[PDB]
Image 1 (cartoon, protein in one colour):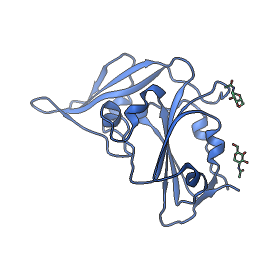
Image 2 (image 1 turned 60 degrees about the vertical axis):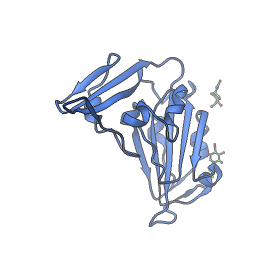
Image 3 (image 1 turned 120 degrees about the vertical axis):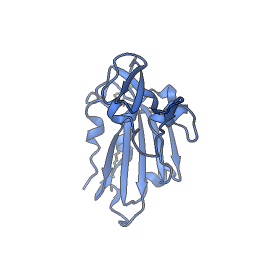
Image 4 (image 1 turned 90 degrees about the horizontal axis):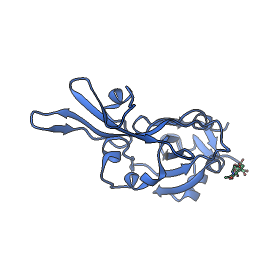
Length: 198
Ligand SMILES: *[C@@H]1O[C@H](CO)[C@@H](O)[C@H](O)[C@H]1NC(C)=O
Ligand SMILES: *[C@@H]1O[C@H](CO)[C@@H](O)[C@H](O)[C@H]1NC(C)=O
């Protein structure tokens, strides 16, 4: 039975700090078919050749995705500094991963656009003298996710519950929507729970 990538093709992809995670087990995949639907600008594979990626057998296959402007590609690079790795998404390199940046063609209709691209500029607890920043663990959500989900309708809008404080930055989506996918694979327990279609 085939792995169904319909969910990422349907609806509006979330802001980066609230990325969507799809996990596939006990199914076969056709990654070429999924990727061919997008205009790929960048991609980067760690501990994989995309060939090995498109033809290997794993115990599970995880896909994280979110709306993301391609020109912010460097902030997603391994070892990068700044708000994106700090407060939004820090890639987990403990497993073979591939990061793909792509533009959604208008010919692809089921994907809808948000009004704004968005990311967190900070996530902290107030100390006594300054801010005690809280940084993303690899592959995990910001601890400011609950606050961030309150939404941002202006630039540098803040949210707090007393303890935590977050601040988001927003800007209009101009042109075709651009996205990021992080494909991750695991070699556990289950040898060939996930294999390439044939
Ligand atoms: C995977 O999808 C591609 C379309 O991009 C198609 O050409 C190919 O035949 C498919 N592979 C299998 C095994 O179905
Ligand atoms: C959208 O239409 C075709 C069919 O999917 C696609 O291959 C093509 O790249 C797109 N058209 C453009 C980009 O003008």
